[PDB]
């Protein structure tokens, strides 16, 4: 009860020292390990991955959680180094703890936290909590401080982080929401970025046919290109191929709707596609979605 | 009330001496006895504010107290900015102790107020007052020349030019804390040894620009040093260790975590001339071998607390020496041997002679068994030993 | 390494000399005493502490090997100090007489905690202090001291 | 793609077990993992209990003390003691206080000042001082102010205009302009447009069409295309359809069977989906959804505010 406090401090120290030994750590995970059976740290570093042995987490999060609250509540002081390290450990364990992120915002405003350090923190928490809403929210707050070419390196690292978080979590709304935001506020809808994203991301959509967030992101790319032809046609053909190769995905038929809606700013070709689909299809889901597409089609 | 019948004024004031200002004002409303007690001078001596951000309090205390405010802690009161502290300063000229730790909205403007109105300051804590520049140290050097204690921790935009201005006026500093002032270099160390000959305590943690040139100078200029922190100062060598031994016979505390280059040569020279060492933190002094501990067991009879974390080369041998120290038989209480991979159960049997040990750390010492721990706890129930088990 | 202590009422207590020199007063008396071979092994006289208070003190000293602030008391001490008001005041006096700064801090912080978080009449009720202020004076003081 | 309802799925409402479950709900590790939303957790649990005629089972006084102890000097309310204030937990605490008719145990004026202060010049609202924009916050803002009778305290026309710029061409809404449409967000905006009397700028046929395609063959509702059905998204989709009067566009019976199939017959509580573990969050939305489909053992629920309609009538009959 007092031997545990020492242990939790030790494990906090072990996490910080992991990052000194390897500042290229790029992933964290929980190592299922309910028993402390040897005198080794529960912090296991193998190559670039940082594993945390589960037996210690039941001690580590309540202590670091309450340390942060006792600080915030003005009953126990933490200095700058401890703030940074206590909140680092909390966000590794529970990145939806907004108060923990908010303490780093202040540390960043005061100048003692390099913002780039929080971009790395979020990136690593996102390897374990890819949908974490607060982490994305914090990450946008940091990014907007850094805009008040380094932009392109930021934009480019956001695309990869969002890509990483989308591959780790099915239909990751928050990852793609963040990716949209970045386009809006960091790239300000730069037409060549929208183009490079449209091409980079066609591969990813090919591989994630049931993921509607990814297709909406392509929908966003195209609409935003509009607001500044061959791209729409090539997106309908892409949808024709995907619908044909992977019958029965509501995401693909929903994508074709959105994309065909934009192209319509003719419908016989789309009727015959629905006719040809419904005549020769074995998938029962595919028939639902094709019949559903036509009821949508005729209200035009 | 029993309280008044059994406890005399001297003790009642001790009770009230633990009370916030809000609670102290309510006791003033209890009785005529408790009124004279609630407002007695000794209760308005020190204020530690534990309040809400949304300030005027510091300004209202400045009036209700005024002349007798001597110590004022505002640690973590992000509410306060220059305006409140101007008002408090012009009303509390006898203040001897000001703690502004973490008060982030503090500008050069308040050190100017302090210079104008608080010439009796002996203790200024500026930890994490990030908006403070070199100019603040110039103002403090003009109006706060009796300063004995200054803490600039994590005041990262302070440079050698501020340090120079500060010590050129505050020649009487006995304690100077500069942790996390990463722009400080050897010239700033040289301004310190030039002017702060009465320096007892110096913190240079994470001031990793400094080198032996600066540290050796500090030892030449500060012969009264008792406490020195150089953790994170990777550039240092045994040369700084030789200069310490030669110049600082009163050394009690030496923190040199992460100083990789330090070797037995340095520590033998240090040990023989420094017979008053009590704390030594040598975490990640990898080159250190059992020989370093040998000299410590001979030449350091009052050694109190030793960290050998990550000193991989340390073996059960050096631990036997420590335990057969004059310091080990009674005056060692804290020993940290974690990530000393060679330490075994035998070292825990050695340290059964250390009847004074309160705290033993063995994290990542994989040769150490649950059995060894249990028999050490059994011989020394005084000791809390700490491993991952 | 054990000494005998005699309380005010004549009961004698065997106490280890180490846990007992947490008392600066007791350590003083030992230093004053011998250094004596030829005595009658008389205990250390403690005329200003009775056996019940001593008991509580020795138990407090055995449990310990080991800022205007009261949220600070360890939980063993909090439990230890859940006594009637009379004995806790006696423990303050004892801690002061015997100069046990740890015990005098927790006990004073404990009485201080009984005052915090209450209204003036909640104070006078806890400690049965008679309010000797007229409404004129009570209104006044809840005047100056009111700022807040 | 979907769940399959087993032949032994609960087909009737087990009100007493749900009230026992919520009444005994309550470990230290996972208490800390959840504390960042404690206020709303309490709102789910109190609200389902009052919908079930069981609110008296709960400790009114420790709740009100907790809320009183969560208002910061800026006026905003945090999820727990010592957490930072956020609009989400200010809505929750105000909902809780509305259930307990104890709105005035906190400083209503400073709550109003806190909400008002989060609006931005384009009409949008931030969730707290740090400035995250979300239509969920436009909803939380007007819901809190409506409950306090203080909708005039913000710029309503700007707030409406902003929310309308989040309308997608598919009829839905997301967190911001350009966002993917999303049932939870559609619920917030729909609820926003109901509190502020602007539902007529919504193409009800478009939105209700997007919404009714959330029903899967199992009867359950998902939150977006090709997601599993979910009790919580079932409630938000059902609530939205009620608000826009397109509730006849889903099969209410199959959805009722889906929600009922999410009860645990042994423990009480609803899971997100049959087979999964129950929690108080889905317990509220399961019971609220059933009240909306016509379960007469449950008090009628308001679709905008997720509270007993009786509690909002008490609000709407006043100075107001
Ligand atoms: Zn759900």
Image (cartoon, rainbow, N blue to C red):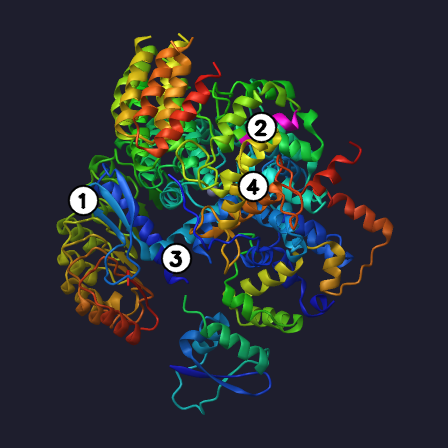
Specify few, some or many for label 2: CA neighbours under 10 Å numbering under 14, 14-19, or 20 or more. many
Q: What is the span of residues highlighted in magenta in the rendered image? A: D187-196
Q: Position of residue D163 (x, y in %)?
A: 55, 22
The chain letter under disc 3 is A
Q: Evaluate whether label 3 is on the same chain as label 1.
A: no
Q: Which mark is residue A5?
A: 3
Spatial CA span between label 3 and label 1: 29 Å
Residue underneath mark 2: D190
Spatial CA span between label 4 and label 1: 47 Å
Query: Vertically, is A265 above or below C45?
Result: above
Of tags 3 and 2, the one toward the viewer is 2
Looking at the image, residue D36 sits to the left or right of residue A209; the answer is: right
Which type of secondary structure does the marked residue at label 4 adopt?
Answer: loop
**Viewer-nearest residue: C135 or C39:** C135
Q: Quadrant of residue A97?
A: top left
Spatial CA span between label 3 and label 4: 27 Å
- Whether label 2 lies within 8 Å of ligand 1 gets the answer no
Specify few, some or many for label 3: CA neighbours under 10 Å numbering under 14, 14-19, or 20 or more. some
Specify few, some or many for label 4: CA neighbours under 10 Å numbering under 14, 14-19, or 20 or more. many
Query: Vertically, is B281 above or below B149?
Result: below
- Whether label 1 lies within 8 Å of ligand 1 gets the answer no
Residue underneath mark 1: B260
Q: Evaluate whether label 2 is on the same chain as label 4.
A: yes
**Viewer-nearest residue: B258 or B54:** B54
Which type of secondary structure does the marked residue at label 1 adopt?
Answer: loop
Spatial CA span between label 2 and label 4: 25 Å
Spatial CA span between label 3 and label 2: 49 Å
Dot 2 or dot 4: first in sequence order is 4
The chain letter under disc 2 is D
Of tags 4 and 1, the one toward the viewer is 4
Residue underneath mark 4: D78
Of tags 2 and 4, the one toward the viewer is 2
């Amino acid at each position: 009860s007092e031997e545990v406090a020492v242990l939790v401090q030790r494990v906090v120290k072990d996490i910080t020292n992991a990052f000194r030994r390897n500042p290229h750590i790029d992933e964290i995970g929980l190592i299922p390990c309910p028993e402390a059976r040897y005198n080794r740290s529960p912090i296991v570093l193998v190559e670039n991955k940082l594993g945390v042995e589960s037996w210690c987490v039941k001690f580590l999060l309540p202590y670091v959680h309450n340390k942060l609250l006792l600080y915030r509540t003005r009953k126990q002081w933490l200095n700058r180094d401890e703030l940074i390290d206590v909140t680092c450990t909390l966000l590794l364990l529970n990145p939806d703890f907004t108060t923990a992120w908010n303490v780093r915002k202040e540390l960043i405003l005061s100048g003692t936290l390099n913002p780039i350090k929080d971009l790395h923190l979020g990136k690593l928490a996102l390897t374990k909590f890819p949908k974490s809403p607060e982490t994305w929210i914090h990450r946008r707050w940091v990014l907007q401080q850094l805009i008040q070419e380094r932009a392109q390196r930021l934009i480019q690292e956001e695309m990869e982080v969002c890509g990483e978080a989308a591959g780790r979590y099915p239909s990751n709304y928050n990852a793609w929401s963040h990716r949209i935001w970045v386009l809006q506020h960091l790239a300000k809808l730069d037409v060549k970025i929208l183009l490079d994203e449209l091409s980079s991301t066609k591969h990813w959509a090919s591989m994630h046919v049931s993921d509607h967030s990814g297709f909406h992101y392509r929908q966003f790319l195209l609409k935003s290109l509009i607001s500044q032809p061959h791209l729409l046609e090539e997106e309908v053909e892409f949808s024709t191929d995907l619908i044909d190769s992977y019958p029965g995905h509501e995401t693909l038929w929903c994508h074709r709707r959105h994309i065909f809606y934009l192209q319509h700013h003719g419908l016989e070709m789309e009727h015959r596609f629905i006719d040809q689909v419904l005549s020769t299809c074995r998938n029962v889901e595919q028939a639902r979605f094709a019949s559903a597409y036509r009821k949508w089609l005729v209200t035009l | 009330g029993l309280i008044n019948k059994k406890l005399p004024k001297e003790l009642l004031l001790r009770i009230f001496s633990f009370l916030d200002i809000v609670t102290l004002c309510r006791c003033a409303q209890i009785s005529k006895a408790w009124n004279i007690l609630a407002l007695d001078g000794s209760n308005w001596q020190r204020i530690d504010l534990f309040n809400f951000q949304t300030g005027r309090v510091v300004e209202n205390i400045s009036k209700r107290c005024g002349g007798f405010l001597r110590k004022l802690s505002l640690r973590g009161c992000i509410g306060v900015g220059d305006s409140s502290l101007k008002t408090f300063a012009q009303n509390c000229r006898n203040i001897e102790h000001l703690n502004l730790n973490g008060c982030t909205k503090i500008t050069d403007s308040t050190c100017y107020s302090l210079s104008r109105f608080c010439s009796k300051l002996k203790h200024l804590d500026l930890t994490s007052c990030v908006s403070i520049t070199n100019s603040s140290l110039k103002g403090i050097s003009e109006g706060c020349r009796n300063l004995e204690y200054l803490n600039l921790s994590w005041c990262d935009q302070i440079t050698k030019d501020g340090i120079e201005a500060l010590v050129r006026g505050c020649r009487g500093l006995k304690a100077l804390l500069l942790r996390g002032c990463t722009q400080l270099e050897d010239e700033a160390l040289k301004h310190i040894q030039n002017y702060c000959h009465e320096l007892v305590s110096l913190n240079l943690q994470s001031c990793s620009r400094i080198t032996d040139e600066g540290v050796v100078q500090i030892c030449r200029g500060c012969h009264r040093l008792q406490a020195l922190c150089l953790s994170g100062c990777s550039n240092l060598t045994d040369a700084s260790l030789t200069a310490l031994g030669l110049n600082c016979p009163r050394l009690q505390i030496l923190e040199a975590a992460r100083c990789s280059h330090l070797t037995d040569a340095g520590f033998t020279l240090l040990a023989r001339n420094c017979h008053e060492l009590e704390k030594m933190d040598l975490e990640e002094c990898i080159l250190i071998t059992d020989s370093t501990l040998i000299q410590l067991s001979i030449h350091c009879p009052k050694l109190q607390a030793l960290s050998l974390s990550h000193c991989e080369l340390i073996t059960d041998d050096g631990i036997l020496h420590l335990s057969n120290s004059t310091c080990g038989h009674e005056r060692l209480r804290v020993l940290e041997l974690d990530n000393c991979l060679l330490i075994t159960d035998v070292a825990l049997e050695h340290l059964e002679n250390c009847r004074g040990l309160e705290r033993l750390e063995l994290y990542d010492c994989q040769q150490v068994t649950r059995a060894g721990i249990k028999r050490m706890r059994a011989q020394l129930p005084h000791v809390k030993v700490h491993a991952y088990f | 390494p054990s000494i005998k202590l005699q309380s005010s009422d004549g009961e004698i207590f065997e106490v280890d000399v180490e846990i007992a020199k947490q008392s600066v007063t007791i350590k003083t008396m030992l230093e004053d005493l011998g250094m004596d071979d030829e005595g009658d092994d008389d205990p250390v006289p403690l005329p200003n502490v009775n056996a019940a208070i001593l008991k509580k003190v020795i138990q407090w000293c055995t449990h310990h090997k080991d800022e205007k602030r009261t949220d600070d008391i360890p939980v063993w001490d909090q439990e230890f100090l859940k006594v009637d008001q009379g004995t806790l005041f006696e423990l303050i006096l004892a801690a002061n007489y015997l100069d046990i700064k740890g015990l005098l801090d927790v006990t004073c912080k404990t009485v201080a905690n009984m005052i915090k978080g209450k209204t003036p009449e909640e104070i006078r009720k806890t400690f049965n202090i008679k309010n000797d202020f007229t409404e004129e004076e009570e209104a006044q003081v809840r005047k100056e001291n009111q700022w807040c | 793609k979907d769940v399959i309802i087993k032949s032994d799925a609960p087909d009737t409402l087990l009100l007493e077990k749900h009230a026992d479950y919520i009444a005994s709900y309550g470990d230290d590790y996972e208490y800390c993992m959840s504390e960042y939303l404690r206020m709303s957790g309490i709102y789910w649990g109190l609200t389902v209990m009052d919908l079930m005629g069981q609110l008296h089972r709960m400790n009114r006084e420790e709740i009100l003390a907790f809320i009183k102890s969560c208002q910061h000097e800026c006026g905003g309310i945090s999820a727990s003691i010592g957490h930072d204030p956020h609009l989400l937990y200010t809505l929750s605490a105000v909902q809780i206080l509305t259930l307990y008719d104890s709105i005035n145990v906190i400083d209503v004026n400073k709550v109003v000042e806190y909400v008002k202060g989060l609006q931005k010049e384009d009409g949008s609202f931030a969730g707290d001082i740090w400035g995250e924009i979300d239509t969920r916050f436009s909803f939380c803002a007007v819901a809190t102010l409506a409950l306090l009778g203080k909708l005039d305290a913000i710029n309503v026309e700007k707030a409406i205009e902003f929310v309308l710029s989040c309308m997608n061409f598919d009829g839905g809404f997301g967190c911001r302009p350009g966002s993917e449409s999303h049932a939870g967000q559609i619920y917030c905006c729909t609820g926003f447009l109901a509190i502020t009397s602007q539902l007529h700028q919504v193409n009800s046929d478009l939105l209700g069409w997007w919404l009714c395609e959330r029903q899967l063959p199992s009867g359950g509702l998902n939150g977006r295309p090709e997601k599993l059905p979910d009790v919580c998204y079932s409630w938000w989709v059902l609530a939205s359809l009620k608000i826009i009067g397109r509730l006849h566009w889903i099969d209410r019976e199959k959805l009722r069977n889906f929600i009922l199939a999410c009860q645990d017959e042994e423990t009480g509580g609803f899971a997100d989906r049959p087979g999964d573990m129950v929690d108080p969050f889905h317990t509220l939305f399961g019971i609220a959804g059933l009240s909306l489909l016509g379960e007469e053992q449950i008090k009628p629920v308001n679709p905008v505010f997720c509270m007993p309609e009786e509690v909002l009538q008490r609000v709407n009959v006043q100075p107001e």
